[PDB]
Image (cartoon, rainbow over all chains, first blue to last red):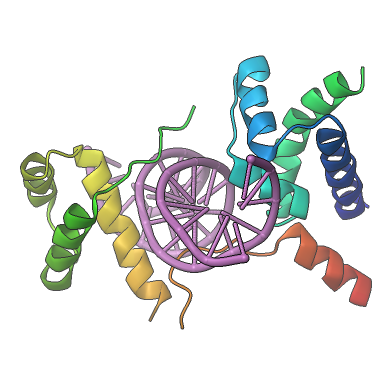
Length: 133
Length: 22
DNA sequence: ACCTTATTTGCATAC
DNA sequence: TGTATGCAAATAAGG
């Protein structure tokens, strides 16, 4: 079984990590140093608990397997949005949930943010409003 | 009370439990 | 380019 | 201190 193979691998990976004294964050950083693709402590945690989708585990397994084999021998950084800035965006959302591209650019300029971050903030916020009904 | 953020759908953990149940 | 729906992924923090 | 997880920023793919 593919699912059972992922279960057994996650277990073997976790055991070897712990046997060597690595934290989850350590091994995520190690994978960036050695193979150029760092992952967060959060992701390592989810992988070891099988709290990722099937496709997602199948994607990461060969990367984690490179480190395990040694042990047995690209995305942009997540932008932090200040509380007062988030509240400014939220109050705008309440009366204009879908600003135009021009307005998005103006908001970014006024708030000293990147236009793409503001664009994506509104996209995600619309999706949230759907999720929470 | 409502979950605010995005959740993974169909984790391997859940799929394994679903398979082992039937 | 830039919306959509869907999903991956990481801060921040409570254990 | 290290791990789990709420919230959500970034990305994937179609139009």
